[PDB]
Amino acid sequence: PTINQLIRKGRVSKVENSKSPALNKGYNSFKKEHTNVSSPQKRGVCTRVGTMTPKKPNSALRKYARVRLTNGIEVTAYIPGIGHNLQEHSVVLIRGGRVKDLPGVRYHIVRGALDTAGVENRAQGRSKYGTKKPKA
Amino acid sequence: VMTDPIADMLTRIRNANMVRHEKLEIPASKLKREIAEILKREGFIRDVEFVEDSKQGIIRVFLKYGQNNERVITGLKRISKPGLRVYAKSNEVPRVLNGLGIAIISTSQGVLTDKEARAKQAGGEVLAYVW
RNA sequence: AUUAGCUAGUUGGUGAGGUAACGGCUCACCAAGGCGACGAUGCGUAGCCGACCUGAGAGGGUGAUCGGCCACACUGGGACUGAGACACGGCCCAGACUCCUACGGGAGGCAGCAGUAGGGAAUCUUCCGCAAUGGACGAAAGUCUGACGGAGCAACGCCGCGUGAGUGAUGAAGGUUUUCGGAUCGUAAAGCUCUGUUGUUAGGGAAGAACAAGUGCCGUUCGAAUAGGGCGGUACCUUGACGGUACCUAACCAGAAAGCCACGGCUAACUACGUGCCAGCAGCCGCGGUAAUACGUAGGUGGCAAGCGUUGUCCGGAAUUAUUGGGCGUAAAGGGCUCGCAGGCGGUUUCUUAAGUCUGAUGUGAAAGCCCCCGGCUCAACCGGGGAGGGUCAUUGGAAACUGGGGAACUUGAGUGCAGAAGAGGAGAGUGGAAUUCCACGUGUAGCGGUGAAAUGCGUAGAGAUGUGGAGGAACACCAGUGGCGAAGGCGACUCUCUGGUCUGUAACUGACGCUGAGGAGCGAAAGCGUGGGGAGCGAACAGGAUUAGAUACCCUGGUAGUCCACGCCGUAAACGAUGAGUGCUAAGUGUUAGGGGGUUUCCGCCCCUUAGUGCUGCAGCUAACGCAUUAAGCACUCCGCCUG
């Protein structure tokens, strides 16, 4: 609008969140607080691995991890591969991936982590899902 | 109230273009009288006339319709609003409609056009845009 | 600003001390100031800058390396010597911790180079050399250099080169697909010919290295001196970590060497099997319950290349915070409306001033980097040379139209006088007239009352209807009308007292005195609240009779608060023109409320001109469409609020 209206209020600029909140904060022990690291990827510990359903028209039951990171925050992640490898108390590296279909989980588990061996018999999609080149 | 004198004379020229009136009345201050000679001397007015009255004076404009149905003045625009004083320098003299249009510039050495401010190389206030 | 009050050595003065130096810097005295809506104090946050990245530019993000400066040296405090510190590898003290002790005592500080622990998604070699650059001291040689010089690690990134190349149709073989004719993997292989970047072998072997120092002279300078020097010139001599590394020379072989991603639409590229809401894809729309070009596989394409994808970041596209570069009738958005301090903006004419503005000159914004142009490295990347650019910069000298300031005039803006006219504008005390009920009574009998139907309620104690009379409240027909007036909410019986603004008529006056207005102030229907007053109708809550599968509802007869009054408070609504206030301008036609001017007319009247609200149909233009249209949502401008799915 008018100019003197703009000067003593300013343009109140638009603040946007991240694509995933639980990658943006790290932990340090003896400080006993909750640092702002903005690291991409973290290694986490699974606690409960049950499975459940997606929400709507797609109805085919998913894999539903629940992982606990090194920040201290327990965020349910997702297992992408064709069948899993994980059991309780494992090493789980997490990249930022949005799952529209499942309610609440916004974290893939990197199939191909330190503990996640690659999915069985996969040729296409080699870099994803952690499989080596089979034989050359 | 009236808030500025030059705004309500330029749009009054513009609001006569959509009806194609022959003549106008503008209450004719000093810088109002000198804008009209600029448009007269450079192809936008048939003839301009001064009226000496007792109240405040009136200046009147014969609009220039030289061809079939083709308004020479196709729009005006006042820039340096009272609260935004566009001081374009002499290095960066704003030419409008690049090749075609004029902008009236009030300089320290008279209220000039683009050209008379250009070669004399002195800038200042920029009071209007003219298509 | 979901931090509005904060500071007493604070803030002032005087003197004193103290500091290299000015000082409440320290202390005495005396004073009460200072800091603040331009946001103090506080709190969370963070080293700053040339610059980096991005954007077309305006801007936005980041402040790593290299270059500037400050701060810190386990945490904290003091202090010495020294030109310079409150000292990164110095002292003294405590705090934690490590190490040693014969327990009395001591020593220690890697955010120096490396390296390790540990943290974490994650970051490198415990090398060589002082040859060059640098410093340190010394008369010099020299000495000392984890500055630096190079080597080593990781595709970490940019750039540079490969991974064979010509010929070769037979469209080989094989693979995949198939309507079994074929199609494609295709000149792709084989064959033939080919060079050797690099790979491999053997050789040659830079510049970086300039020197110092010592010798030689000549010049000059001191000198008791041709002693002996000093510098200055030239002359000889001598000095390599990288490293026999780059490099070049010749010899050798297609021999050493390509992958990941995509393939419905965005988006370049598709088929076959598997599969059957399951397994699984997914950035977006969304794909699969039996023919999945979207899942998985295979073939075949396409993408880019020593890399490719995914991931988290920041910018962009995002005009989607809009200064350049939006909105507000209904899409997100006008404050309910006012009176207004601060802040914001300014009629006309003229003199003057130069704060803003314009412009020169000078000084400066180091270098590297961006950018202009050359040159160097086998080109490139990189590096070098020169130049520009970058400052709301400072001083100085100019310009006077516009803005700010000052001096003086004009009257249209606004206001005052005066002469009118309109009014349900407000507040006050009082006044009636129908009508409802209540009650008194006459007259008079079986029901009225009520609904979709009916019942509850009322009635032989005399209702209802009807006649007079009485109390009492609240509402004020008719006039009544996109009619009046107020800023809005709102105000309709009547009269009086008191009081606000409105509009016309000019001209008598003032000489811009105006508009808007964050906070602040006051008003603001109905509901509700507290204290009493008053309670005839009406009437939430509740009760009853029906209705209904249910009726905590619509209907039904009652019925409490309420409404009503004075006084105090809440301060909200579709507080609506879903349109913030003012100023001008932009075809008409048309009523209608109040005027005024005229034209024949005392008229009535008609007609025309004209201010002000008040409505409707309409042109240009605005609008996404409906619509809006001199009462704008047209074109412009000043101010305030509001919105960013």
Image: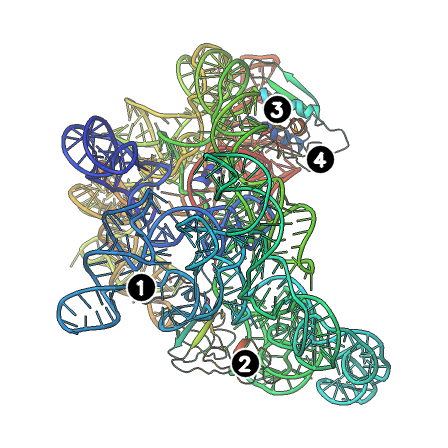
Instruction: Categorize mark 4 by other alpha carbons within 10 Å: few (<14), some (14-19), many (20+).
Output: few
Q: Which residue is mark 4?
A: B100
Nearest the viewer among C635 and B97 is B97
Q: Nearer the viewer, mark 2 or mark 4?
A: 2
Please, which chain is the residue tagged with disc 2 on? A
The residues tagged by marks 1 and 4 sit, at their Cα atoms, a distance apart of 69 Å
Q: Which residue is mark 2?
A: A131
| Magenta span includes A38 | yes
- Mark closer to the chain start, 2 or 1: 1
Q: Nearer the viewer, mark 2 or mark 1?
A: 1
Q: Secondary structure at mark 1?
A: loop
Q: Nearer the viewer, mark 1 or mark 4?
A: 1
Instruction: Categorize mark 1 by other alpha carbons within 10 Å: few (<14), some (14-19), many (20+).
Output: few
| Magenta span includes B119 | no
Where is residue C573 drawn, in percent x and y? 39, 47
- CB under 8 Å between discs 3 and 4: no
Three-letter residue code for mark 3: Val
Are labels 1 and 4 assigned to the same chain? no
Are labels 3 and 1 assigned to the same chain? no
The residues tagged by marks 3 and 2 sit, at their Cα atoms, a distance apart of 78 Å
